[PDB]
Image 1: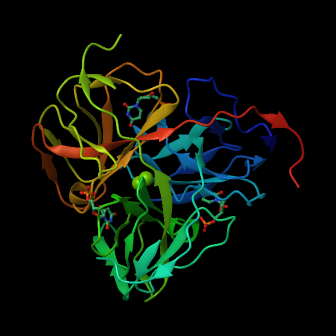
Image 2: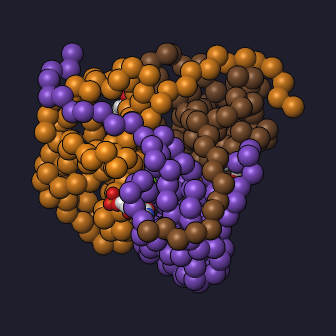
Length: 117
Length: 117
Length: 117
Ligand SMILES: O=c1ccn([C@H]2C[C@H](O)[C@@H](COP(=O)(O)O)O2)c(=O)[nH]1
Ligand SMILES: O=c1ccn([C@H]2C[C@H](O)[C@@H](COP(=O)(O)O)O2)c(=O)[nH]1
Ligand SMILES: O=c1ccn([C@H]2C[C@H](O)[C@@H](COP(=O)(O)O)O2)c(=O)[nH]1
Ligand SMILES: [Mg+2]
Ligand SMILES: [Mg+2]
């Protein structure tokens, strides 16, 4: 797919997602929420959406990823919503790996009001 | 698919999930976990499951979604498990958008005890 | 698929994921992150990855699952990264159900540097 920016990395065939980098240094105190920018935009292929999910290295540090749904039509820059849910302060270096992007299939249903049994 | 209730909204073709609304007003103090009700039930199509995932607007407020797996056979009402992982108190208005439902494909494997190399 | 270990349970046709058990007793104080071991390894089918996601029973207790992406090529033992984001202490008994594994499809794209409109 078409992407702009260098905040996203090519992956191998055997990996599920693309590593996303932090565009600038970020400090987070316990309980702080900050939207970390990546500087990348992309054109998800028709019929698919992107899921931002955490990496074990940052997660093991007590950092979590919130939200995480990239809609196919989105063209803005991708941002990773991170929170320090640990009890110690953390600094994420610039261009550090903070999350992963996984491309998944779309399923559109019509909503039918009825009675589910 | 068949649904009952008005706590879920039709989406566009370009969106990955359906917005879920809160059935009643909810207050959450830092560190509090509450199962927010939506009032909706649904009949997921055979071969698929539903994933409840967070929205960037509430997530940016320090709210996270836990659990999140709707099994195809479930017919009960859908509930969103939310926690205030931020350091400030939050109130979710009635019928406010709190999460998103995404329909994904099922893959059933048989478990073979063996030796993975 | 081929698995080794008894920390993972067969599921029904109607369930989305396989329950994962804790290999040993674990205590977690508010705000503590610990990688809970399961003792299971597996050979994900080619073309798929595994997603570790939370269960409503533990999630309703204020426990969250971080990270969660099993790459198809991984052969090591599966570990569940858990954090107590609640305000009370928790003990997870040995062989207790702590998470769920869901198998999802892989989508590999080539990264094309361009200009997204
Ligand atoms: O963690 C996230 C979640 C969302 N978006 C973007 C891309 C989506 O298309 C858009 C959607 O908004 P919500 O539906 O999450 O509010 O926001 C991000 O950059 N990061
Ligand atoms: O956040 C959640 C998670 C689960 N369920 C429901 C629908 C599922 O079929 C059922 C499954 O239970 P667990 O397997 O998550 O314990 O609970 C919810 O309403 N909300
Ligand atoms: O919650 C998790 C996340 C990852 N892994 C394993 C399997 C993956 O193939 C590997 C990948 O590492 P990261 O890409 O998450 O850093 O770690 C786990 O056991 N548990
Ligand atoms: Mg999550
Ligand atoms: Mg979380």
